[PDB]
Image (cartoon, rainbow, N blue to C red; front, side, top):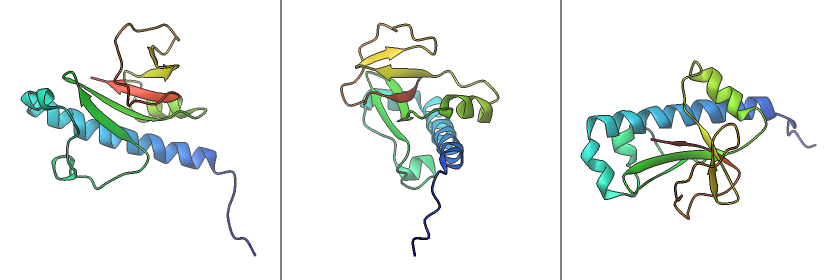
Length: 123
């Protein structure tokens, strides 16, 4: 007997977007309060975010900008937009390049530790 329920892609992206937005907002709020933290790099902690560890959203502060990202899936962009009232300003990483949502290169050098095929927020 396998009890596994397959094909839960929409449920998965719904929760991935909610997690992304939760972490994004917590990171954004902390750095808005404490802009001097940008210079140090690395990551904010679980205590600073008030959120425990998570497996489906990653972040990094580099060259005083913060980057938050998740593995791209069909409709994940639309779910992020839905759950942010169309307000999140998002981008993509493809072949080591930052692309806007219309696929045009944004000529910033990305940290080398961000993977391809993610949706990303840089702020």
